[PDB]
Amino acid sequence: VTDNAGAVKFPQLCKFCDVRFSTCDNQKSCMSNCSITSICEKPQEVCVAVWRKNDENITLETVCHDPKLPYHDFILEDAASPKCIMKEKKKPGETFFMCSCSSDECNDNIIFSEEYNTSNPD
């Protein structure tokens, strides 16, 4: 089975759970629990994911968006990356994590180590 409808006449596909609770605690390869695949409304739009711990609650929101528009008063530009490369973001009063990629199913698994901790730290 393939993830493409045919040659390449379809828009980008991605996970779209909207606001959902999550148990992603430490960084380094986390995971989302929704399994809902949705197609991006436009080819220019990418896959943006955000994990936020509010005191005693963790939540991950996932939705397609255009990398040319700012988000939360910030300019989005890590979407060109095929996989999550942005490493956590400091929100005043909150720990907001930034992450945007342009690959089909890219929000089901989040990457917070590039080489998946290949360094093998002790």
Image: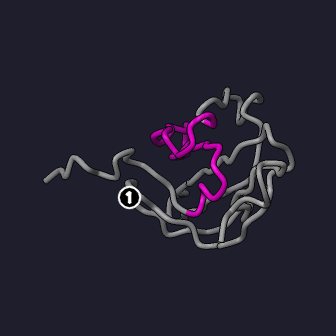
Q: What stretch is highlighted in magenta?
A: 79-108
Residue 80 among those drawn in magenta: yes
Write down the residue under mark 1. 26
Residue 67 in picture, x, y percent from top left: 72, 33
Secondary structure mostly taken by the magenta-highlighted segment of the chain: loop
Does the stretch in magenta take in 53? no
Please tell me which residue lies in front, 52 or 101. Answer: 101
Front residue of 14 and 57: 14
Q: In this view, does 86 lie to the left or right of 45?
A: left
Q: Which quadrant would the N terminus be assigned to in this image?
A: bottom right
In the image, is residue 97 above or below residue 3?
A: above
Please report the residue visible at 29 percent of the width from the left and 51 percent of the height from the top: 117
Q: Which amino acid type corresponds to the residue marked 1 in the rendered image?
A: Asn
Q: Position of residue 19 (x, y in %)?
A: 71, 62
Disc 1 secondary structure class: loop
Q: Out of 4 and 96, give the one closest to the viewer.
A: 4
Vertical placement of residue 41 versus 75, above or below: below
Depicted 15 relative to depicted 44: above or below:
below
